[PDB]
Length: 166
Ligand SMILES: CC(C)c1ncc(Cl)c(C(N)=O)n1
Image 1 (tube, rainbow, N blue to C red):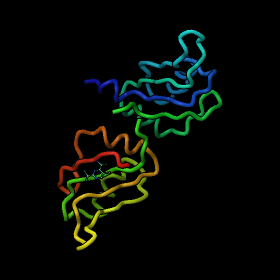
Image 2 (cartoon, rainbow, N blue to C red):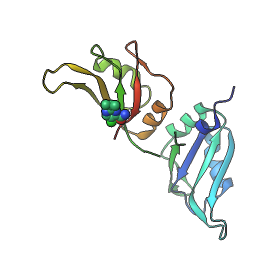
Image 3 (cartoon, rainbow, N blue to C red):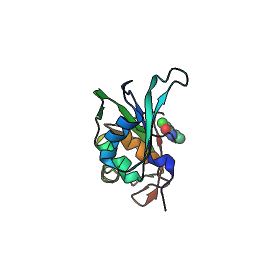
């Protein structure tokens, strides 16, 4: 049962114009089996457009490649991002957590997606009561990208709504 191809793709921006299908593949094959690897080029001049994409055999291989950033490919630090579901942000909205969810509930769950920098449990401006939603800020966008493509998030027994924030 193969994961959907879209979830196995990495868009690589910031390429050296000298990077080729072959040199992009040789680099990113260090972190998994590549079923596809393409440098985008102008149709007339064949000059690189400065970006391309690689497709791994599994999502765990995508994770391995992202965890090995920064990637210097043919002498240039490139910018890998998971394919769109790009709104590149480090913060999520977490809704549906009700009044009994605390900081440690959110931390213990979300810390396995990435390094957390801020947890903000929202409270009512007048009463101080919890409003039932929170924001979590990570040190990097790939955490958010992994989070929002999941169908489900269960935190503190609550089925939560999670979206990219701002
Ligand atoms: C009131 C709820 C719907 C809300 N407030 C703020 C944000 Cl930033 C989001 C979101 N989906 O990102 N959702």
